[PDB]
Image (cartoon, coloured by chain):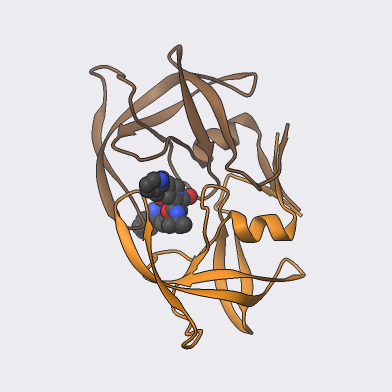
Chain colours: A brown, B orange
Amino acid sequence: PQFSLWKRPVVTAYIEGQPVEVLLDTGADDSIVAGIELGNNYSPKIVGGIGGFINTKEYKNVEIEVLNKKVRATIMTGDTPINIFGRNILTALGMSLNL
Amino acid sequence: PQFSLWKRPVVTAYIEGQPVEVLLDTGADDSIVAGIELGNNYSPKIVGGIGGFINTKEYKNVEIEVLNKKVRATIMTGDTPINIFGRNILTALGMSLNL
Ligand SMILES: CC(C)[C@H](NC(=O)c1ccc2ccccc2n1)C(=O)N[C@@H](Cc1ccccc1)[C@H](O)CN1CC[C@@H](SCc2cccnc2)C[C@H]1C(=O)NC(C)(C)C
């Protein structure tokens, strides 16, 4: 798969079986999703960007199906305006930025 | 060129001849740089990030030289911890996200 960047590179991912629409984001160091309940086993963390920071819950070894692949990665849940799949996941998938 | 996403995809760009280090950001709709003065023909813009909104100065038709290409694009200026090149520039450069 190749994504021109005219539109936002958004895809459907399933996180612990729940479909979510996510942004493939090379500028994001971490992955953060909203509207999913991941349970009790997390660590309270913070994540920031333009405009400041937000509280998050960090989950490890989360099952993810996306772009026809199956991976386990660290995902944060928090009040993000858009769901993000950052470098942690992109790397696991073998995705690259090319010119 | 190809960028594996193990490290942040950061390159040197010259903005109206001035060198700056920029992050190639598929998740960003706009481009925002700090610490270059681009002059007085700007219009103020409010831009939203993961943690909040910031005030920016938007400049149009800025000459950019990056990855051996020359483009003219819109650039905002404001307090960003990291200089970012978003989809507006990535598109004009002809970059893609591939898997
Ligand atoms: C998701 C985060 C883990 C991620 N941040 C980082 O990876 C990160 C790295 C180093 C840092 C150093 C100091 C302080 C913060 C740092 N944050 C991030 O926000 N990345 C940004 C770019 C970035 C990198 C570094 C620092 C700051 C910002 C993302 O790619 C682009 N981002 C994706 C989330 C949307 S949410 C914004 C919004 C509001 C309402 C509705 N819809 C959208 C906004 C958009 C963005 O920042 N876009 C620009 C740059 C155009 C403002």
Residue at coordinates 36% horizontally, 40% vertically from top-left? A81
> In the image, is B58 to the left or to the right of A78?
right
Task: Find residue B92 and report its image quarter.
Answer: bottom right
Residue at coordinates 62% horizontally, 30% vertically from top-left? A93
Q: Position of residue A88 (x, y in %)?
A: 50, 37
Q: Nearer the viewer, residue A63 or A83?
A: A83
Q: Position of residue B78 (x, y in %)?
A: 39, 71
A57 over A48 or under it: above or below: above
Task: Find residue A30 and report its image quarter.
Answer: top left
Task: Classify the position of the N terminus of chain B by image quarter.
Answer: bottom right
> In the image, is B52 to the left or to the right of B72?
left
> In the image, is B92 to the left or to the right of B37?
right
Q: Nearer the viewer, residue B47 or B35?
A: B47
Q: Residue furthest bottom?
A: B39
> In the image, is B81 to the left or to the right of A46?
right
Residue at coordinates 49% horizontally, 32% vertically from top-left? A22
Number of callouts in the render? Answer: 0
Task: Classify the position of the C terminus of chain B by image quarter.
Answer: top right
Q: Position of residue A38 (x, y in %)?
A: 31, 19
Residue at coordinates 62% horizontally, 44% vertically from top-left? A7
Q: Position of residue A44 (x, y in %)?
A: 22, 34
A19 over B14 or under it: above or below: above
B23 over B96 or under it: above or below: below
B26 over B45 or under it: above or below: above
